[PDB]
Image (spheres, helix red, strand yellow):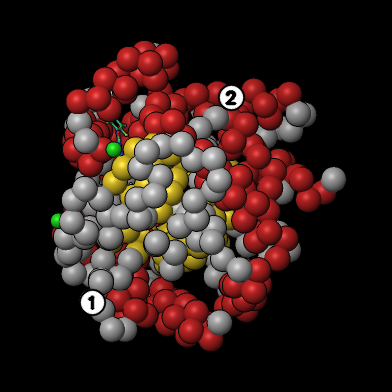
Amino acid sequence: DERFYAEHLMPTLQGLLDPESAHRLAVRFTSLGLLPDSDMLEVRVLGHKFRNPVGIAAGFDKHGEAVDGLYKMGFGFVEIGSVTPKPQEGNPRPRVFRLPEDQAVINRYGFNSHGLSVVEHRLRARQQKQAKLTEDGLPLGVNLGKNKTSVDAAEDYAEGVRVLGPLADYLVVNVSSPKAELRRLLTKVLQERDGLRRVHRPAVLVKIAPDLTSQDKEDIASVVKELGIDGLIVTNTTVSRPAGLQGALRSETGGLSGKPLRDLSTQTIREMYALTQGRVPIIGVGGVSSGQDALEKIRAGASLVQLYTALTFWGPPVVGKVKRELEALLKEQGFGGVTDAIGADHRR
Ligand SMILES: Cc1cc2nc3c(=O)[nH]c(=O)nc-3n(C[C@H](O)[C@H](O)[C@H](O)COP(=O)(O)O)c2cc1C
Ligand SMILES: Cc1c(C(=O)Nc2c(F)c(F)c(-c3ccccc3)c(F)c2F)c(O)nn1C
Ligand SMILES: O=C(O)c1cc(=O)[nH]c(=O)[nH]1
Ligand SMILES: [Cl-]
Ligand SMILES: [Cl-]
Ligand SMILES: [Cl-]
């Protein structure tokens, strides 16, 4: 199955369809269930149980259309979004580009979004089914964005907390799509979160870019610890273009994802974990396509990982591949389970 998808099915789909069409078709098949975990992999973090540490990253299911199909694919948690307060169309097409020679993607969707109300009703339609999933170790995250024309960014995020916070196990404030300002924004987000009833009160995480200065990262770490933010997601796509990219489309505007981002992300995880003294959970994301990629991020300080771009090259079988390879490496390196490996590089 893994070799069939990787060598025949996916490159044939890649040859027939532009990338955005292929993505919409993938969302449709996934939402319909048309698709091909040991105790070692279980993680307790963010007030929840995660049956395995491999999640689908924000951007694949922007509108909350495919959540149950994504669990069926084998992900330990699903993050939907980003969702903006009002519906908006995003940038003109084409707005996403494959770099097959680099195992990379560049995108400038621009927060195309069905908007909070539509996503609210979509998640309400399965709210009790989610409550059982979460209880069974399959939590749901909701990533919040802001409309293009908004004047008050904090009020857009506050709206998302009030509308989708009650349906989420965790919320993501994505201030990273391609110090006192951040403190102001996050104080307002956390106040809105704390005003939700306890059974409907999610964890709040901040998702950051890999393109931050050292000053930026220091200031983020300080605010996150000061305010009691529950976690970090590290990282979004990069607006850098590392030397060595071969794809003809490498100079398209947008955020770069996939293998060229991987170690830039891992190093950002490493720094943020050290700057927060290992006390702030990190979801690590960027260029994960194997168990080794996942364990490097875990050893660098991630309690959980996500992927997206690998799914677009290798198809659904990549999820089970990453999990199988991660379990094998954990045993080889003598860890009793994922939990013991979190942050392990910092104890050498
Ligand atoms: C097509 C595409 C769309 C994305 N949209 C978003 C988004 O709406 N919100 C967000 O926080 N990140 C989004 N991302 C970033 C991913 O969540 C992730 O941080 C990044 O792609 C690195 O992971 P990867 O290398 O495994 O793809 C998007 C990524 C891609 C490739
Ligand atoms: C976002 C994206 C995809 C994408 O998502 N492709 C894709 C996928 F991510 C899938 F997961 C499947 C799939 C295959 C079988 C069953 C269910 C889903 C698929 F066909 C796909 F094209 C792609 O090829 N390019 N870009 C930018
Ligand atoms: O354009 C988008 O919607 C988008 C792209 C991306 O790479 N990251 C993000 O947060 N939003
Ligand atoms: Cl459009
Ligand atoms: Cl393309
Ligand atoms: Cl509710």
Given residues 5 and 114, the one toward you in this image is 5
- Ranked by sequence position, the earlier of labels 2 and 1 is 1
Seen in the picture, residue 310 relative to 213 is either above or below; the reply is above
Judge depth for marks 2 and 1 and give the one in front.
1
Answer left or right for 19 relative to 243: left
Answer left or right for 287 relative to 152: right
Q: Residue at x 35, y 33 (%)?
A: 312
Q: Amino acid at mark 2?
A: Glu
Look at the image and tell me whether residue 46 can be seen. no
Q: Amino acid at mark 1?
A: Thr
Q: Position of residue 66 (x, y in %)?
A: 25, 41
Q: Residue at x 68, y 59 (%)?
A: 271
Answer left or right for 195 relative to 346: left
Tag on residue 325? 2
Q: What's the CA distance linking mark 2 and mark 1?
A: 44 Å
Q: Position of residue 321 (x, y in %)?
A: 50, 24
| On-image quarter of the N terminus | top left
Q: Residue at x 35, y 50 (%)?
A: 252
> Which of the 4 image quadrants contains residue 227?
bottom right
Residue for badge 1? 149
Seen in the picture, residue 12 relative to 154 is either above or below; the reply is above
Which element carries disc 1, helix, strand or loop? loop
Report the number of discs: 2
Which element carries disc 2, helix, strand or loop? helix
Query: Label 2 CB, ligand 1: below 8 Å?
Result: no
| On-image quarter of the C terminus | top right
Given residues 135 and 294, the one toward you in this image is 294
Q: Residue at x 82, y 49 (%)?
A: 347
Given residues 51 and 112, the one toward you in this image is 112
